[PDB]
Image (tube, coloured by chain):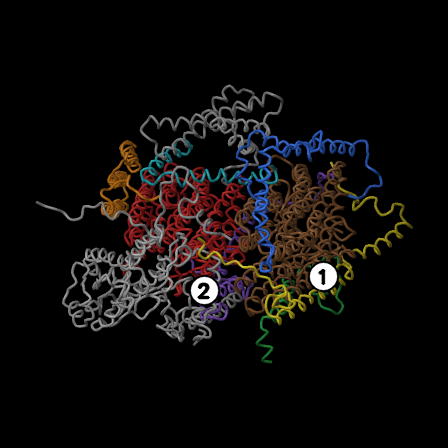
Chain colours: B red, C green, F blue, G brown, I orange, J purple, K cyan, L yellow
């Protein structure tokens, strides 16, 4: 069949697919850095 | 409607911010009017004979309503003097103020425009805006909840679920059922305002998300019960499971997120020694469920709406948050027990 | 090795789910450490074992 | 989100020799179909005539659905020997109207994005001629006509332009002799009263089309089959007073969104009203949905599909 | 199973058969069209 | 219910109206039997036959509840006295027995010494 | 230990291939039910709490084992149905049973009233979707709406009841903490406090008034007969009447007096109708009213002897009525109608299933001590200590207990079957296995019924 | 007015009922006028001739409910002892719902919901004790 | 006090005028102007007699927004006369 | 407390009081994380895509967004419950007269019959 | 009499009367902005005269 | 007119194209499910589960109380006069009224 009359999505976009996988990396590093900072602040206070 | 349509939509977003961040009584009047001049064009859009009737009915019932608010603003100059949105002070001013707020939120004697205005919108995008506009005058009520006489605020809550619980029974129009679902839920809104200011804003968080998910499920065009009926067999069958889940949560049922506001409304009211009023809230809540129960029979039962015409091509709607928000709308019972404190 | 892994994949999850439930619900007693040696009803002094029994 | 601030915009690189042409309502015999193929000298793209399997001609993947998979009891040969009570009759024509409306939306989408002249064989403004000819004889009930008029008022008004170029051919009353000479044996032995009524209804269809200030050119059987005569007549005639000349910013953008999606265009095409010749039975609908999902064509649908394509998981 | 006769009971009219108001007709499928005519349309001068 | 003489063969006459009356009964009896005969004597069936008379018998008790009872009259109130009434009848029976028992516990003991169960 | 492996049944049915499904859902459920008997039975003098208050221990609940017993059995009789339709539809209505099993475990385990309430009404949602779909006959909605608007109309008054207690008297929570509770002073303001806690359980446990919730759910069959076993679980799912009456209102029994008299007439009149009825499923539906009416009588007496009979009858009825509905389903799959008179013929066509028909029918009566003799007789013995008059009314009911069973037997024990041509194969290997898996657990309770009745036993 | 409603609670403390019956008509009369005002929105045919006709049927019947309720409460108080009871007002509540069947020739409706109207009327005098509160602040 | 007693009575007449309808639709928008006119007198006098200086700008802002509703709602009136013959409250289709 | 008296109005999280220590790998966070995975299962039901579980790998965005917002949302939960308790204990300490203590009794209670 | 009609007549009693109360709001007031604004005149008078608050 | 409503057909496995089976379709799935794992629960829950029930792990002080009672009887008989019950958990209460 090979999807006739041109499909709306080819499947690899890279412009949209690449950044969406990139945003998860930006979120994961940001959360652990504040997590270590919160424990360091709690130990300094108490 | 090209680029400037987003700008018109932005002024409603910015309009509520003026109401949110305010200290002056004339500043919120500006904030309400920012919505007045910006919803009407989206109410029209395509220009229809039904749209012309709805937009005029939306204007006249709401512009006169805000004009009653300006009287209460001017009584705050005659009495108590100061221009601050902290307290209402005068009982004479509160009578005209609460009735002006009832024209937008209380609904019990001012529901009349809602079933005609909500039906009159030609587009699904306009349905979201009326459920989002109700956030604006709630910010006013959260500021001036003391001093206002509770005898004529709780009557706007008790009677609203009565007329909301009967006003959807003789309606087949899908927009009309959701119009009376507003008034039914608005009774729960005007009940927590006298009894503990918190969870009143969380009632909005549950409601607005639940209603925004509802109309975005109707992005596949449906305006009547019979038009939403032909969806299980002819159209997408897995889509109707999410319509079922959202409708079950619209009524008071425990394993869903929609029961979680109904928890604290009764809980805070029972703490104030009142038992006879929350009992009446629970029995009238059953009448609300019945509309959603009949509308779940378009998703559960066969009902025979096969039709000759069939769709094979994949549907591509707008769907801004029609995937993330229904997951919170279906299950948030275990997820949000201590979250009452997080909102306010 | 190829015949067993391809055919069975969901069959392992249920007995392993019982073990996962066994470990999780047992470790909740570590949150409730109060009244272990105190209150004379089943109280006994330790001789060799630490904190009587978990 | 729709992008309009970008380089791609309406009216740009269009309109200059890109208007749609239609050769419609020319009796039962396909005489307009042959002349439309030669009419694509000035026009860039030419579209095929719609039948029973016209919506599934492209749709998802290449091959058309077999008999029951496309539409329950739908055949062009079955309408030639039409039977009253329990059968095709109206539900084939309702499927025929929905198929012509779907291909019109894609042709308009082909016109709006990248300005190319698309010629359509038998448009949506010709199906009412085909229905009324059969209504004169005892075949279609009065209640089914009211079902047709309700769809007619909703679907048509959403699209702004009808047609810039209209070709109407009026042949001899002895057109049945030409149909008998044709290669198809199933199409033969058709009723003479239905063909005569089709020409009579077409006479009251060209006049309201001309009333909306759309350019129309009449051609006889002797004037038929001409490439030089048809192309020169369309080029010399200028479009005036027609509803095609609309707003470039507001009107053109709104019509483009409705034509872009296939599901959005056919959303109003399905009626909530129940009819005996429309197949309302849910029991047959459950079995048909199971067979369509099991089919190697669409199955999972929208781009990615197992045992058909499958390029990437993400 | 529910048939076409059961669907006509919950059809678009009044949900509840009308007591007094039964003259109100059902609305159109995708926004009703009202009066095409009843307009002046083009002025005439002597 | 029975009369002075049991009805089995009492009061029978040939006449003309009674002769046609038996002809009317056999006309329906043979009509409903032949449609059963056409359904029973073929191997192609395999299954349980419907019969419209038996379905309407079950429909008489399971349904036709609220289509009826629209003439309430005095017959419905007599049925209410036979239903809600006997519930009030035992209210003056169980209470009188309990008041007899409760007085005995406080003064002049009647309960057995070898009683411990409940 | 109990929850988590039950939740893992949800990804099990979806991940497995289309040819299997039913093999994985039944086999894996049986080994979880074995482990429930392995750990829950251990208790001291007063049954000590399991862990933190999410799911707690059992004090007087061997009824959890019954839910684990039906956990695979709610899949066996539903095999005849659902097979004709789509593979995705099969997976959906197995997971709705898994969700039912998820919420039903939570109700009996968790020693609470506040969080118990949001699990009490939570069982209604999956059953609603179960009843409103797959119903062969019509009026699914005239039973589906009645399923909620009877229960939710009575149970929503618990929000104004339970919260009112915790705002004044400490907190409800553990129940093991609930000894703060002072006896009620008995006043006109305290009337609606007692009624709101009762009316919720007056619906699920059927009486004489507001009893029509149950026959509509049974006659209008959800799916085949395996979902009707879940409708039996809903009757015993309102077990909190054992907990509320003992703890929340100990002094209050004067207001219980009219409610006993209502349930006492819900024994003669409910049995009389269960004689001349046409539907085979209805003659189990009305006998289930009277059998569960015996429990309501026992609770409101509050004697230590009555709770022994109350806890026994919850398990007794939970495996005898469900057994009877499987026999009703076995005739419904062959004759395709629930009519008793039309579906007539045992032993001649159904040789081995007729012995299962006998064992199921006689268990409704007082047989040699299986469970129902430890159930029914214990209540009758306890009613005499309440009042001497009771056994005059209760003895008449013991005559009509035969008239449920024997009338179901005799109207099927005629070897005519002239109109019927179907039912060639008597029973499949799974169909006979269903009948054994209901009676043989009760036959094992003959040796030791300690794990059948245990409120301080 | 709430001052009219506050007068209703002071009289039953004694034995006098001659002025109590006069006060009950104003409670039922004013409440009937509220329903009578909303019935104008149903579009009345002609002017005044049928306008008074719609207001006449609603106000006169609603005032009759209150008037009999005030009378029956005092008959039940004078016969036998006991000053105030929920059982005492339940008999008076049944008489108030009995006259709704006199409005239309059907014998039921009012008599069918006689136990429903009688219980709700009893609930008003259930809240004479400190246990029930309709509106509260703390 | 004394001057405020008459303009409050003038406010109630303009309030009823909004709530009253007989055939014509134009009266409502005329009453919306009158309502804002009566509010303009009430606002001005309170700031003028009891001096504020900063708050005297507030009725000037109120004057601007009064016209905004009396133009954008007034524009909808003309749209009724495009669909229908003439503007009537009696002429409505919605239920 | 609903109205702020000591706490700063309009805060990103708290900032005035930071010392509390947020939960690490909590059972509450796992349920919000499960809903993030659940939102990435029903999104393929809307836009018809092969397999809900083994489909598109844009599910990681849905899980992370629920965790990141949920962590901040639960941080406010631990903060607001602490302030609610802090003002409660301070009210007893400052006033003293409002609170009363009673321990050890020998009071008679009415016994029930049957 | 009882087990199908009279004992049932508790909830159908609150359906037949509920639908009558439902019809008095939906079918009532046949459109018209005129009629809805005539009802708002009374609502202010209820809050001032009928209900004692300022 | 029904159009598409007529589709109902009687279906039964019985014995035809199944030989002897309980599961619908495929002989390989039937034997491995309906006779093996169907009866594996019959062997573990019923037969191996019969050892538990109440027999073995004492079960709420049913066997413990007998040994505890007998030693308390013989001790109180030799020294005291009152047998077991006389004043249950009451020794010097602080008045009554």
Residue sitting at the far left? E46
- Categorize mark 2 by other alpha carbons within 10 Å: few (<14), some (14-19), many (20+): some
As helix, strand or loop, the secondary structure at mark 2 comes to helix
* Residue B189 rendering spot, x and y as whole percentages: 44, 47
In terms of image quadrants, where is residue B167? top left
The residue under label 2 is J43
Q: Where the N terminus of chain D falls, by quadrant?
A: bottom left
Between residues K22 and I12, which one lies in front from this camera angle?
Answer: K22
Q: Residue C37 carries which label?
A: 1
Q: Residues within 10 Å of mark 1 (few under 14, many from 20)?
A: some
Does residue B93 show up? yes
G8 left or right, relative to G353:
left
Labels 2 and 1 share a subunit: no
Q: Is residue J64 above or below residue B50?
A: below
- Coordinates of residue B247 in the picture (x, y in percent): 47, 53
Can you tell which of label 2 and label 1 is closer to the viewer?
2
User: Extreme bottom residue here?
Assistant: C1
Task: For mark 2, name the chain.
Answer: J
Specify the label residue G157 is tagged with.
none
Q: Position of residue F93 (x, y in %)?
A: 72, 32
| Image position of L49 with respect to B45: above or below | below
Name the element at disc 1: loop
- Residues B72 and C11: in front is C11
Taking depth in this image into account, of B209 and D34 the one nearest to the observer is D34
Q: Distance between the residues labelled 2 and 1?
A: 53 Å
**Residue G157: where, in percent of width, then height?**
56, 44
Q: How many marks?
A: 2
Horizontal arrangement in the rendering, residue G340 relative to residue F64 (left or right): right
Quarter-of-image position of residue H74: top right
- For residue B21, say whether it is visible: no
Which quarter of the rendering shows the C terminus of chain D? Answer: bottom left
């Amino acid at each position: 069949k090979f999807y006739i009359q041109e499909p709306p999505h080819g499947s690899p976009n890279w412009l949209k697919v690449g950044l969406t996988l990139g945003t998860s990396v930006f979120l994961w590093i940001y959360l652990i850095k504040q997590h270590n900072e919160d424990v360091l602040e709690y130990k300094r206070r108490n | 409607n090209p680029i400037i349509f987003i700008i018109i939509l932005l002024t409603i977003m910015l309009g509520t911010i003026i109401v949110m961040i305010s200290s002056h009584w004339l500043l919120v009047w500006i904030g309400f009017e920012m919505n007045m001049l910006a919803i009407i064009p989206i109410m029209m859009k395509n220009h229809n004979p039904r749209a012309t009737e709805a937009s005029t009915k939306y204007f006249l019932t709401q512009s006169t309503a805000s004009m009653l608010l300006m009287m209460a603003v001017i009584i705050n100059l005659m009495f108590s003097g100061q221009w601050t949105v902290m307290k209402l002070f005068n009982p004479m001013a509160s009578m005209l103020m609460t009735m002006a707020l009832a024209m937008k939120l209380g609904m019990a004697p001012f529901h009349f425009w809602v079933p005609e205005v909500t039906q009159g919108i030609p587009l699904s995008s306009g349905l979201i805006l009326l459920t989002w506009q109700k956030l604006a005058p709630m910010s006013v009520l959260y500021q001036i909840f003391p001093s206002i006489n509770l005898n004529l605020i709780l009557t706007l809550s008790v009677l609203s679920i009565l007329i909301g619980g009967w006003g959807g029974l003789n309606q087949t129009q899908l927009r009309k059922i959701m119009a009376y679902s507003s008034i039914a839920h608005m009774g729960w809104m005007t009940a927590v305002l006298p009894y503990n200011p918190t969870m009143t804003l969380l009632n909005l968080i549950i409601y607005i998300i639940m209603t925004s998910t509802m109309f975005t499920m109707f992005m596949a065009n449906s305006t009547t019960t019979t038009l939403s009926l032909s969806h299980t067999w002819n159209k997408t069958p897995i889509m109707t499971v999410l319509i079922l889940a959202t409708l079950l949560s619209m009524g008071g049922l425990p394993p869903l997120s929609g029961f979680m506001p109904k928890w604290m409304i009764i809980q805070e009211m029972t703490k104030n020694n009142s038992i006879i009023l929350p009992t009446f809230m629970a029995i009238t809540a059953l009448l609300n469920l019945y509309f959603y129960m009949r509308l779940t029979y378009s998703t559960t039962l066969t009902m025979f709406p096969s039709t000759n015409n069939m769709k094979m091509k994949w549907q591509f709607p707008l769907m801004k948050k029609m995937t993330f928000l229904p997951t919170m709308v279906v299950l948030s019972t275990m997820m949000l027990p201590l979250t009452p404190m997080l909102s306010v | 090795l190829l015949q067993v892994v391809r055919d069975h994949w969901v069959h392992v999850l249920v007995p392993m789910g019982f073990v996962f439930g066994y470990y999780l619900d047992r470790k909740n007693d570590e949150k409730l450490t109060a009244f272990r040696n105190k209150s004379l009803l089943y109280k006994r002094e330790l001789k060799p074992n630490e904190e009587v029994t978990w | 989100x729709x992008x309009x601030x970008x380089x791609x915009x309406x009216x740009x690189x269009x309109x200059x020799x890109x208007x749609x042409x239609x050769x419609x309502x020319x009796x039962x015999x396909x005489x307009x179909x042959x002349x439309x193929x030669x009419x694509x000298x000035x026009x860039x793209x030419x579209x095929x005539x719609x039948x029973x399997x016209x919506x599934x001609x492209x749709x998802x993947x290449x091959x058309x659905x077999x008999x029951x998979x496309x539409x329950x009891x739908x055949x062009x040969x079955x309408x030639x020997x039409x039977x009253x009570x329990x059968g095709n009759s109206y539900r084939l024509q309702a499927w025929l109207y929905a198929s012509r409306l779907l291909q019109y939306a894609d042709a308009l989408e082909h016109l709006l994005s990248t300005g190319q002249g698309v010629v359509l064989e038998r448009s949506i403004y010709s199906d009412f001629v085909f229905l009324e000819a059969m209504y004169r004889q005892g075949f279609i009930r009065k209640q089914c006509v009211d079902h047709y008029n309700q769809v007619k008022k909703v679907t048509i008004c959403e699209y702004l332009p009808p047609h810039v170029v209209v070709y109407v051919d009026v042949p001899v009353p002895e057109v049945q002799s030409r149909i008998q000479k044709k290669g198809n044996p199933h199409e033969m032995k058709i009723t003479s009263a239905y063909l005569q009524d089709i020409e009579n209804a077409y006479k009251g269809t060209f006049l309201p089309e001309m009333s909306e200030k759309c350019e129309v050119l009449q051609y006889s059987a002797w004037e038929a089959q001409d490439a030089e005569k048809v192309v020169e007549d369309i080029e010399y005639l200028k479009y005036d007073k027609g509803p095609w000349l609309d707003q470039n910013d507001r009107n053109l953008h709104k019509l483009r969104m409705l034509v872009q999606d296939k599901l959005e265009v056919l959303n109003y095409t399905s009626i909530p009203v129940f009819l005996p010749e429309v197949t309302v039975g849910a029991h047959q609908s459950d079995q048909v949905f199971q067979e369509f999902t099991e089919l190697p064509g669409r199955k999972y649908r929208a781009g990615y599909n197992e045992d058909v394509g499958d390029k990437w998981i993400w | 199973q529910p048939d076409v006769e059961w669907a006509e009971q919950y059809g678009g009219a009044v949900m509840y058969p009308t007591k007094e108001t039964a003259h109100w007709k059902p609305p159109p499928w995708n926004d009703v069209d009202p009066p095409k005519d009843t307009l002046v349309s083009n002025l005439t001068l002597n | 219910x029975x009369x002075x003489x049991x009805x089995x063969x009492x009061x029978x006459x040939x006449x003309x109206x009674x002769x046609x009356x038996q002809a009317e009964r056999l006309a329906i009896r043979s009509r409903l039997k032949r449609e059963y005969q056409l359904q029973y004597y073929d191997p192609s069936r395999r299954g349980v036959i419907e019969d419209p008379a038996l379905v309407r018998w079950t429909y008489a008790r399971s349904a036709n509840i609220y289509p009826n009872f629209r003439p309430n009259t005095k017959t419905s109130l007599l049925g209410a006295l036979f239903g809600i009434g006997p519930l009030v009848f035992w209210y003056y029976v169980f209470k009188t027995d309990r008041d007899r028992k409760e007085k005995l516990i406080q003064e002049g003991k009647l309960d057995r010494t070898f009683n411990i169960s409940y | 230990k109990y929850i988590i492996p039950t939740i893992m049944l949800m990804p099990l049915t979806w991940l497995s291939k289309n040819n299997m499904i039913w093999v994985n859902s039944t086999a894996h459920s049986l080994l979880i039910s074995f482990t429930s008997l392995l750990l829950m039975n251990q208790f001291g003098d007063n049954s000590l709490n399991f862990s933190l208050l999410f799911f707690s221990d059992s004090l007087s609940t061997p009824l959890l084992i019954l839910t684990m017993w039906l956990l695979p059995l709610m899949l066996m009789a539903s095999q005849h149905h659902l097979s004709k339709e789509n593979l995705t539809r099969k997976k959906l209505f197995i997971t709705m049973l898994i969700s039912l099993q998820l919420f039903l475990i939570m109700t009996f385990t968790a020693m609470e009233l506040i969080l118990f309430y949001i699990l009490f009404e939570a069982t209604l949602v999956p059953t609603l979707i179960i009843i409103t779909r797959w119903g062969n006959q019509t009026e699914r909605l005239n039973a589906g709406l009645y399923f909620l608007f009877y229960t939710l109309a009575g149970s929503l008054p618990l929000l104004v009841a339970l919260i009112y207690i915790q705002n004044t008297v400490g907190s409800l929570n553990f129940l093991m903490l609930q000894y703060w509770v002072q006896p009620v002073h008995n006043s006109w303001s305290n009337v609606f406090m007692w009624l709101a806690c009762m009316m919720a359980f007056m619906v699920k446990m059927p009486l004489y008034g507001l009893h029509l919730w149950l026959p509509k759910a049974h006659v209008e069959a959800p799916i085949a007969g395996s979902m009707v076993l879940a409708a039996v679980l809903l009757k015993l799912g309102g077990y909190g009447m054992l907990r509320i009456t003992l703890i929340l209102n100990p002094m209050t029994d004067f207001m219980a007096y009219p409610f006993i008299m209502l349930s006492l007439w819900g024994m003669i009149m409910t049995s009389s109708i269960c004689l001349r009825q046409t539907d085979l499923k209805s003659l189990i539906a009305y006998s289930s009213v009277s059998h569960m009416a015996l429990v309501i009588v026992a609770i409101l007496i509050q004697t230590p002897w009555s709770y022994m009979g109350a806890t026994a009858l919850m398990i007794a009825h939970g495996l005898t009525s469900s057994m009877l509905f499987c026999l009703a389903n076995s005739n419904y799959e062959r004759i395709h109608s629930r009519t008793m008179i039309l579906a007539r013929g045992l032993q001649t066509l159904l040789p081995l299933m007729a012995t299962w028909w006998l064992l199921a029918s006689l268990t409704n009566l007082a047989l040699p001590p299986t469970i129902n003799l430890i159930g029914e007789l214990f209540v009758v013995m306890s009613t005499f200590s309440w009042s001497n008059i009771t056994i005059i009314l209760m003895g008449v009911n013991m005559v009509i207990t035969a008239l449920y069973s024997l009338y179901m037997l005799i109207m099927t024990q005629r070897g005519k079957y002239t109109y019927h041509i179907n039912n060639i194969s008597p029973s499949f290997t799974r169909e006979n296995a269903l009948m054994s898996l209901h009676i043989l657990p009760l036959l094992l309770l003959t040796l030791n019924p300690k794990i059948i009745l245990g409120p301080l036993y | 007015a709430k001052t009219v409603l506050r007068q209703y609670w002071d009289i039953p403390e004694g034995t006098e009922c001659h002025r109590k019956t006069y006060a009950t008509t104003s409670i039922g009369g004013a409440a009937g006028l509220v329903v009578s005002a909303y019935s104008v929105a149903l579009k009345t045919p002609t002017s005044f001739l049928e306008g008074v006709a719609r207001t006449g049927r609603y106000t006169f019947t609603a005032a009759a409910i209150g008037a009999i309720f005030g009378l029956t409460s005092c008959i039940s108080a004078q016969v036998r002892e006991k000053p105030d009871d929920p059982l005492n007002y339940l008999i008076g509540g049944c008489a108030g719902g009995l006259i709704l069947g006199a409005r239309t020739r059907s014998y039921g409706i009012g008599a069918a919901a006689c136990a429903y109207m009688g219980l709700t009327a009893a609930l008003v005098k259930m809240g004479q004790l400190e246990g029930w509160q309709v509106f509260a602040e703390p | 006090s004394m001057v405020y007693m008459n303009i409050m009575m003038a406010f109630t007449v303009s309030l009823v005028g909004l709530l009253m309808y007989r055939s014509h639709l134009m009266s409502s928008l005329l009453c919306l102007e009158g309502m804002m006119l009566s509010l303009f007198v009430m606002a001005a006098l309170t700031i003028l007699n009891s001096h504020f200086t900063l708050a005297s700008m507030m009725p000037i802002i109120l004057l601007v927004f009064a016209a905004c509703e009396a133009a954008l709602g007034l524009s909808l009136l003309v749209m009724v006369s495009n669909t229908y013959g003439t503007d009537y409250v009696q002429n409505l289709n919605l239920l | 407390x609903x109205x702020x008296x000591x706490x700063x109005x309009x805060x990103x999280x708290x900032x005035x009081x930071x010392x509390x220590x947020x939960x690490x790998x909590x059972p509450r966070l796992a349920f919000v994380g499960f809903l993030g995975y659940c939102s990435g299962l029903i999104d393929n039901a809307i836009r018809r895509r092969p397999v809900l579980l083994a489909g598109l790998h844009r599910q990681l965005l849905y899980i992370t967004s629920f965790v990141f917002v949920g962590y901040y949302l639960l941080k406010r939960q631990d903060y607001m419950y602490a302030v609610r308790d802090h003002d409660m204990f301070s009210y007893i300490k400052s006033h003293x007269x409002x609170x009363x203590x009673x321990x050890x009794x020998x009071x008679x209670x009415x016994x029930x019959x049957x | 009499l009882l087990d199908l009609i009279w004992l049932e007549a508790i909830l159908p009693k609150t359906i037949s009367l509920a639908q009558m109360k439902a019809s008095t709001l939906v079918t009532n007031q046949k459109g018209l902005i005129k009629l809805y604004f005539l009802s708002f005149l009374i609502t202010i008078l209820i809050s001032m005269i009928l209900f004692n608050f300022h | 007119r029904w159009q598409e409503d007529p589709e109902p057909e009687d279906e039964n496995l019985y014995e035809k194209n199944p030989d002897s089976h309980g599961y619908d379709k495929d002989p390989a799935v039937d034997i491995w499910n309906m006779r093996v794992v169907f009866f594996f629960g019959f062997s573990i829950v019923l037969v191996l589960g019969s050892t538990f029930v109440a027999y073995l792990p004492d079960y709420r002080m049913q066997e413990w109380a007998r040994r505890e009672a007998e030693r308390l009887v013989k001790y109180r008989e030799a020294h005291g006069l009152p047998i077991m019950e006389s004043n249950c958990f009451d020794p010097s209460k602080i008045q009554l009224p």
